[PDB]
Length: 48
Length: 47
Image 1 (tube, each protein chain N blue to C red):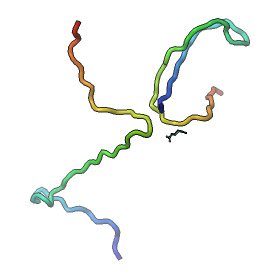
Image 2 (cartoon, chains in turn cyan, yellow; image 1 turned 30 degrees about the horizontal axis):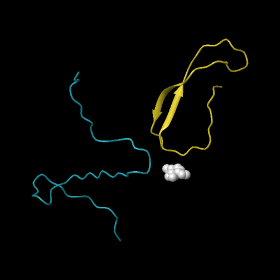
Image 3 (tube, each protein chain N blue to C red; image 1 turned 135 degrees about the vertical axis):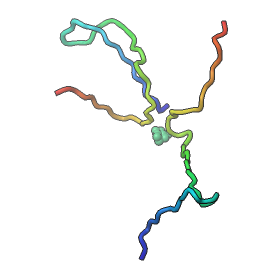
Image 4 (tube, each protein chain N blue to C red; image 1 turned 90 degrees about the horizontal axis):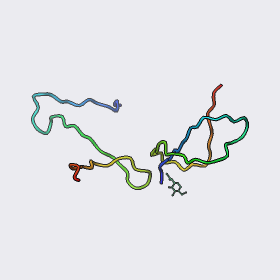
């Protein structure tokens, strides 16, 4: 018998590979529902 | 196209039991990115 979870060992003395690494996933879907977001639209000085 | 469009107007009246004759056009009050196929509606009133 085992409990299904165990903690992760991360310490300030560890070398590369054992050290803690953060992960972010930017899950998204495209072209079904209505859109709400884009990257930036730049602009330039008001020429006349 | 998955957006909602709200248009409105307000005008004062002196009218007793029917809509004003004559004319105006509603302005777009706000637009909302809702994404729902709509088939029925309800209204909320005070009590």
